[PDB]
Image (cartoon, rainbow over all chains, first blue to last red; front, side, top):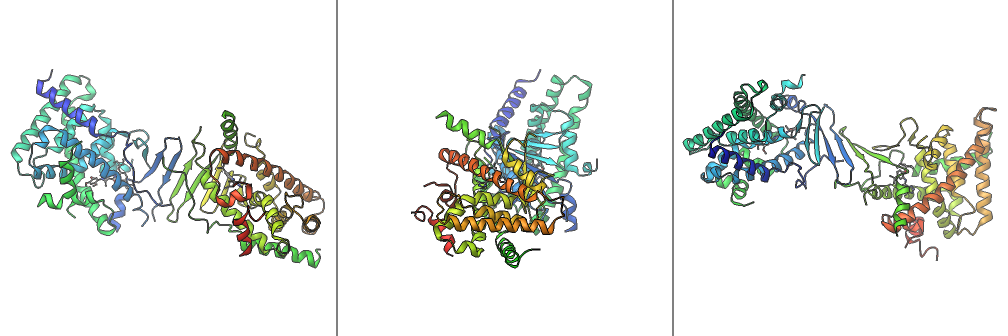
Length: 278
Length: 282
Ligand SMILES: CCC[C@H](CC)Oc1ccc(C(C)(C)C)cc1NC(=O)c1nnn(-c2cc(OC)c(OC)cc2OC)c1C
């Protein structure tokens, strides 16, 4: 049994997730596609994937990427368009949350700047297939091509998928990650921290009310440990992606705002999206 | 051996084939691709498209491979715009091939149109056979490949034609001689100079027959010429079948390029074939 606010808190996060997560990716359209230095290449080989695109008629386009030999940056324009679409649903997810919109406009930008990558990877894990190693995104599919676990990103997705979390546990991780008080640029550190502690208490209470099996022992502490690991991966890959942008500019205008390439003035797209409605 | 006129007859056909056959399909660009998105009229159309089912493969300069798996069953009309662009590109190379031949230029412009109107499909299949892989079942057109999908395929005469013709393992000179015999068919609709085209076709047949006698062993290729003539006869029937299959599909779903509309009878001999007439002047 959870308190009435804990029940209300989960139902709002669940309602916000349903309204702002295009799990079928049907509204993802107008995306770039592949046409018909030593420190950089070591990272891209781990996340090498093949792109599949199913059609409403039943046809299947399949893209096998070129081998290792300006060929490792062919999928990045598409992945930038995909990451931007995912984050636009993340922004809408934050706007629906009542505790988020009541924050100052600068804190809303600072929180989304620090949780952009983390909240996308949590939503990506829900469409990740453990056996096939494929992120099934409705019309689109991303299939990979023992040693991969050395890459923290792939290792994070396999460990998180192994926990077999509920929808409520996924959206609570998004709330705990979004309401991080120690993000760069946050002013209301104390108010955001108070909000984060309530999401953690709600997550801890939910697990005790629905997970009696021994496979889920210490599950709350595992989740909190995964959120810390995901925070480190965020710092690694955000620093890594700036090197690729430095050599081959590929980021969309919204991704450029999130990287640093007044807050409301240099984050014009993010400011406009926070003022717009559903 | 071969007579000096027959030797020069092969040299001209080989020269015409070399100048007009983009064997690597390097100049085939700007083509359409399948996008990322009464009752007896359709019933007869579905039977035609399910016969030949191929998957499209696109190799890239960097090493990437785009692959298109066709759908099942207005969904079976996804590959037609691409094949219309491929056929038109092949037709233009066939027209240029005939224009290089001196025996073809001396014919009236109407007989040139009539011969090209009846042998356009046949000469493309002969060129397509040279890039067909019997083992993999794929037409390798350089960066483009067309792999078939399921004796299940021998039922269609078109696929059976390519496998039987490939088994003969014909030379380049024998292939280009088949094109001349097929191009100079005197019994095409609209042909006027029946005797010239018939005598010209007989000389190409004699040259092809004499070429086999002088460049092949004695007992092994004793009937190779008659096998070739049988394949040309079978190929003429496939042309009549395919031409009728395309008119039914075009009537329901227009996909024909302007050049294909003229060669197939869709809307004087030069009044209804203005595009084909212009390509013969230049
Ligand atoms: C389902 C597709 C995804 C998949 C899920 C983990 O994974 C990838 C797999 C392969 C590749 C290759 C290009 C190497 C082939 C990439 C990814 N993955 C990504 O391309 C990516 N995933 N997240 N982000 C990202 C997003 C952000 O917010 C918009 C952000 O903040 C601005 C920073 C980000 O990166 C540090 C990217 C660029």
